[PDB]
Image (tube, rainbow, N blue to C red; front, side, top):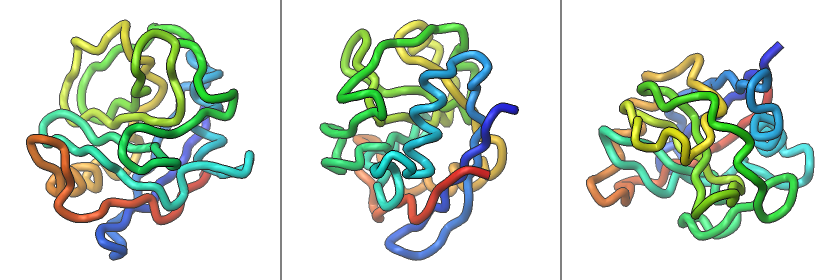
Length: 163
């Protein structure tokens, strides 16, 4: 019953592979629904064609800024921003999907996929999903990051949607 969404990832336009996520709609329904709808594009905007702008190996891959492509944009399906729904789930290790923010109650569209345990984020970022298939593809993406987060090649969501 929890939804599954996919991203098809490309590297300088060349297909890399597919990542699928389970969204924890049973625990964070509002947050899960935002990501789901942005991944299908059903509200007329969303993730398709957007990039992963910041990738720090051994930490995380951050994306979802589909309006400015650099970490300073994005919007939710509820408006520019929405509240921190709850902090029931924790950042327990690689594969966790979590909301980026700029302060309390400032969730938009930006998210990150953790490639390490990031326990210091517990209670500050809302965890709402986890990689189900294709963690190997996230690992391959990570190799195009750097210490300061700039990517060596352009990493994009070529297609996405719901499975």
